[PDB]
Image (tube, coloured by chain):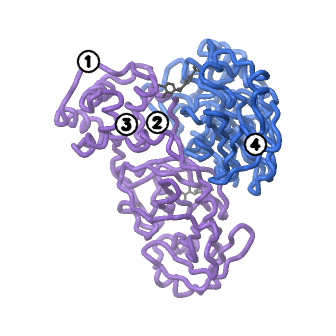
Chain colours: A blue, B purple
Amino acid sequence: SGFRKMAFPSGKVEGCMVQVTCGTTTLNGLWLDDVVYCPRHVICTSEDMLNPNYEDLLIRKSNHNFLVQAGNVQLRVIGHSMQNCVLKLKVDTANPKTPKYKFVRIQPGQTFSVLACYNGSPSGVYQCAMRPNFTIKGSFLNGSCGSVGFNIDYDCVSFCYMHHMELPTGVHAGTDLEGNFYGPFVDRQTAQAAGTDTTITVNVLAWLYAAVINGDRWFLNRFTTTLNDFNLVAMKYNYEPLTQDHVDILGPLSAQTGIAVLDMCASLKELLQNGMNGRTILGSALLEDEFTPFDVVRQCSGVT
Amino acid sequence: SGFRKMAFPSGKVEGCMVQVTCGTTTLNGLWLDDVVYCPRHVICTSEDMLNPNYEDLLIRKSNHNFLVQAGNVQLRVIGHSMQNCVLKLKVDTANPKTPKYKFVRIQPGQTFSVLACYNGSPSGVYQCAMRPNFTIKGSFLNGSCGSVGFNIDYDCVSFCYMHHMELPTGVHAGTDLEGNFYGPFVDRQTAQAAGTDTTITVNVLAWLYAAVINGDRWFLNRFTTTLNDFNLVAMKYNYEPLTQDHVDILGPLSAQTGIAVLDMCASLKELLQNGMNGRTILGSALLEDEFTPFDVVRQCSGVT
Ligand SMILES: CN(Cc1ccc(Cl)c(Cl)c1)c1ccc(S(N)(=O)=O)cn1
Ligand SMILES: CN(Cc1ccc(Cl)c(Cl)c1)c1ccc(S(N)(=O)=O)cn1
C-alpha cells in the first residue's frame, strides 16, 4: 500500500540521450536507431530566437556543424532534415541501446515521465501531466531542451514529448517526436500566454479512488450527483467537464472500491465546495490531478 | 525554472535488480559484483512471520533453495550468509552491469530515490525521505520487498535502503544494505507503532528557498526571528528543532536569494501560525519536507 507520484524507470531512455552542439548552442538529443532527434532551435544564436527563420538558418548548417556526442564518443552525422520543429540527424551508427519504441501524440490530461538531461547526461526523472492548456509544469534549466517525456508498456517506450522552452509565465512547452508543438506554442522568444490551467477531473477522481484503496476515506459522504449537476460545479471551479467516456474509464476503480463513479463525483463536489478544512488526502492538501485512472490501476496492481 | 519532486535516473540500479525465490516466497534482490542482497524474510512461510527464528529457519535452507533469476537467466548460488536482516547470496557470476557503488546508512531527513520492483522487474521510481521516526512513506505492494533506495553522485550509486515491510499503520520500514533496520523496527509480523512523524524543518526551509528562486514569493514577510524563538513554534507544530548546523547547511540558498536563514524561519513561523489561507507554494497546499538543501541546489544547478 501507499501511493506515490511514480515515474517510469528511466534506464531504457538514459541509453538514448546524447549531446547535440551546433555552433555555441548545446542541448540534448534522442538517439534511436541511426537518427538523433533534437529541437530545431539548436541552430539558433542570441539574436536569432526573437523571430528565427529556421529554413534560412538551416541553409547555413552542414552535417559537420552538428556535433553529436554519446557519452564521450562522437557520432558521425551523415544527414540532417527538419521535420516541423525537430531536427533529425542521421548518424552512421545505430544506437546499440535502442529500445522497442513508438512516437505517440498524447491528449491533455495524460501523464508521462520526463528524464531531465543536460549535455546528454541524465539529471533526474519525474512524472507530470499534459495540462489542458497544452503546457507542462516541469523542472527545466537552460541546456535541458531535447529532454524527453515517455510512457513504457512492458519493454516498449512510447515517446510523447520533447522539451523546447519555458514560456514567459514559467510554464513549459514542447513537441511530440514528429516536432509538432502541443497547443499553440511556437519555438520563438515572443509573448506566448497560456490559457486557463483547468484541473483534470477524471484524474482527481482516479486519485480519490487511490486514496480509498490506500485507506484515506474521510471525504466519502452520504451523497450522489449526476454528470450535469457535477459539471455545473466543475465549471465553477475550472475543472474539465466529466463525460460518460471518463465514467467508463473509471469503471475499474468504481468496481474495486464498490463506490459508484457518481458517488465519488458527489464526494469531489463537497471537497470543492467545502475545502479540505485543513485535512489531507494521500499526503496532499490539494486535489491531485497528475494520476490517470490507468496510472492508479498500474500502481495499485504492481505492473513491471 | 520550475521545481519537481525529482528521482535519480534509475538505469544504474535497474541493471542490479534480480528475482529471489525461496520455497513459495518471491521478492527482489540487489546483484552487485558476485553477491545478491535480499531481505532475510525470503526464507519465511505464512506461520513463520509471527515470530520467525531466522537462524533456525536458515539451517533448513541450502544454496540450491535460493532461486536467483536475472532477466530470464538463472544465477548459480555458491554460498549464502545472513548479515543482520539481509541475506548475501554469493553467485558464480559478477553482475556485468555493477555500477560504482557504496553502502551508506542515511540520517533521518535525508532523501533518496526508490526503484519499486516486482519479480526483479522495475515498476517505477520515486523520491522519498527517511522520516524522523525512521519510517518511509513509500508505494510497496506484496512482492516489492528487496526494492532499494539510493542516491547517485555522478557515476557512484550510494545504496541506503532495502525495503522489508509495511507496518500495521500503512507506513514502511527497512534496512541499510548491511541489514540494520532504520529505527526500532524488526522483520516480524507484530505490533510496531511508529513515533511522531515530525516535519523536517531544514528541508521545508530549503523548499521555501526553491520557491523564492522559482518565483513563488508571496509568503516572504517583514519579520525575523531567532533559533530559540523559532524552535518554540517548531515544537508547537511537531517540526524538528532547527540547529546552527541546519543554518550552516542553508548558507548557499541564503546567499543566492539574499534572504537570511532567520528571515526565512520568520516566514515559515507565520505560515505555521496563519496557514496558507488557500494559497499554494510550488503547487503545494502544505509545506513540503522531502527536499534537502543539497537537493534544492542540485535541481537549481542541473547536476548530472
Ligand atoms: C528560465 N529560463 C532560462 C534563464 C532565464 C534567466 C536567467 Cl538569469 C537564467 Cl540563468 C536562465 C528561460 C529562458 C527563456 C524564457 S522565454 N522563452 O520566456 O524567453 C524563459 N525562461
Ligand atoms: C499491504 N500489505 C500486503 C497486503 C495486505 C492485505 C491484502 Cl488484502 C493484500 Cl492483497 C496485501 C501488508 C502486509 C503485511 C502488513 S503487516 N506487517 O502490518 O502485517 C502490512 N501490509
Q: Is mark 3 within 8 Å of ligand 1?
A: no
Q: Residue at the spot x=40%, y=44% of the render?
A: B294
Quadrant of res A171: top right
Q: Earlier in the sequence, mark 3 or mark 2?
A: 3
Q: Position of residue A189 (x, y in %)?
A: 62, 18
Along the horizontal axis of the image, is B139 left or right of B107?
A: right
- Label 2 and label 4: CA atoms lie apart by 27 Å
> Which residue is label 1 attached to?
B222
Q: Secondary structure at mark 1?
A: loop
Q: Position of residue B224 (x, y in %)?
A: 22, 25
Q: Tell me the subunit letter for badge 4.
A: A
The reply to the same-chain question for discs 3 and 4 is no
- Label 1 and label 4: CA atoms lie apart by 51 Å
Nearer to us of marks 1 and 2 is 2
> Which residue is label 4 attached to?
A36
Q: Tell me the subunit letter for badge 2.
A: B
The reply to the same-chain question for discs 1 and 2 is yes
Q: Secondary structure at mark 4?
A: strand
Q: Earlier in the sequence, mark 1 or mark 2?
A: 1
User: Type of residue at label 2?
Assistant: Cys
> Which residue is label 3 attached to?
B206
Q: Is residue B292 above or below residue B69?
A: above
- Label 1 and label 2: CA atoms lie apart by 26 Å
Q: Secondary structure at mark 2?
A: helix
User: Type of residue at label 3?
Assistant: Ala
